[PDB]
Length: 48
Length: 48
Image 1: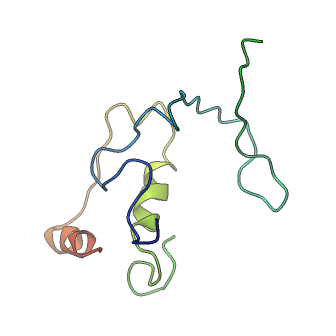
Image 2: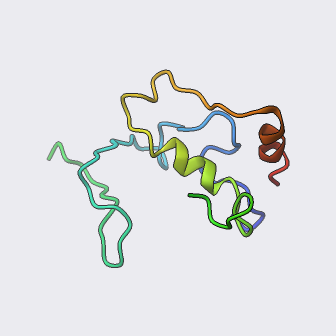
């Protein structure tokens, strides 16, 4: 945030909240990383 | 790598510690741990 503290996983202890804005996180190691025009995060219902 | 060649990153430290955590791979984070000496944990604890 602007104060310089973490938004996700508030402190430097106890990381990985297992909720990104209330929705689960799948760490799929085959998506692109942060490039110029990358799509590094994909949100959606992949069940459908 | 951290950034500046002398110590942690000047602008935003603790960014070099968190990408270290996420550089290791998912299957090894089940039981992994940091390894530092006393005075390095001091430099980590001084991060504000």
